[PDB]
Length: 37
Length: 49
Ligand SMILES: *[C@@H]1O[C@H](CO)[C@@H](O)[C@H](O)[C@H]1NC(C)=O
Image (cartoon, rainbow over all chains, first blue to last red; front, side, top):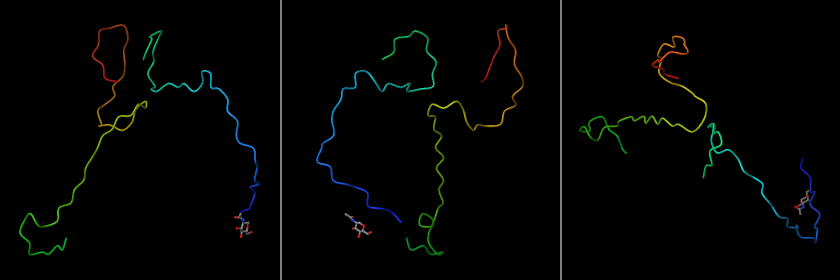
């Protein structure tokens, strides 16, 4: 029931710069102005 | 294992259950059955949350 969709594209994917993204809270622990490494 | 009823102990089948308590980082979960009285404030108290 599924379709061939893929058209061959010569172009490669580009590259960008993740300046400062993708940071998360690795706990459900409350902190208050504590510089934590 | 070819288990047979006329086997000396140490060759008879034993059933095993391994309970493993884990503590990720959630807010809470299952536990023993205590009581859960009430709560108070502004007094030096002995608490369990
Ligand atoms: C396209 O679909 C047909 C069946 O509809 C299948 O036989 C064929 O392998 C498909 N093409 C590719 C490249 O997989």
